[PDB]
Image 1 (spheres, rainbow over the protein chains, first blue to last red):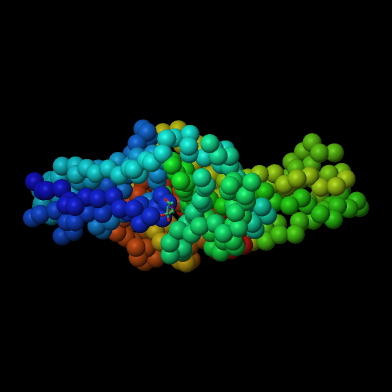
Image 2 (cartoon, chains in turn red, brown):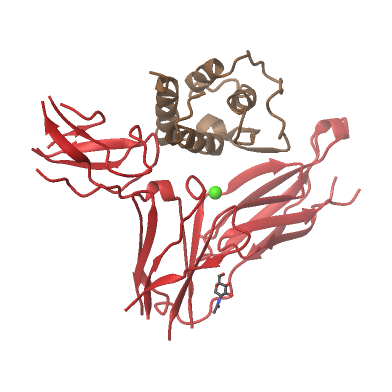
Length: 252
Length: 109
Ligand SMILES: *[C@@H]1O[C@H](CO)[C@@H](O)[C@H](O)[C@H]1NC(C)=O
Ligand SMILES: [Ca+2]
């Protein structure tokens, strides 16, 4: 037999959804820990086995988190069968303040031309937006808001921000809203430019976006990944992102 | 072209990641890799251990050509970070994602 890990705890560094789970070795080769966890409301458990005394991941802070772990002994240790300990359990869940529906609504974001992030929402006193992603020492607040009270945010330059979880919390003073997504998936590019006839051509809009990352749509409707074969529209393709917004159409 | 290798590997990972009705590779666990330089090999050194899963046959074949050297199960040169295993279906989502990143960054090997 073996005992479960000690001090099983979920820690919030305050990164707006990025959480640590921690534990100390149990009492009494190499030792393993099987950690399961999930957001309460999910029917499936995220699973992992580690020799470390901690694990980290992004969670829905709108919801509660529950986790279970159990020491795991390899049969080399035993020199017999595989011994395992009982589940240790912990939970963590943001003390909800204010009455929900005091939580802001219609939250919408776009990463215009993979360059400038905009976030917008309707209310239900004033609102604040914070964000974070790995790299950042701590969660930052928006500077250039969009007033009308704050109902928007226009982000600074987000260096090294794509292809990793992006966290947002909308405080108030009441119920905070939490949002997570990855920038590459939320890009509305600029319409293609310099359309010419010669099979007809056109070229890449002005942006940081490479050409390989583009899918073109053409309503003269049709879809293509080359730039040849009138009006054309664009969108980031699935070699660069998972989802995407179509650019506006070009001129005839 | 030069990106063709990457292009088609990504397609594959996208396939077995939308086309996994039941848990991918019977929910088998594999060593997680540090997703950075010399990781094509780390990725193969990891998955190579999943024997009996055909759903990942292609993927592994494709990987072998990205990796200068041949890789055998139980062999860990490139895989230095070997202190955590994750389910295969997460491994490929994580891998898949990192690939898309390299593609966007125009990095093809
Ligand atoms: C709201 O959340 C931000 C980001 O987590 C935090 O820094 C701040 O302490 C909170 N502010 C209020 C007014 O609750
Ligand atoms: Ca995650």
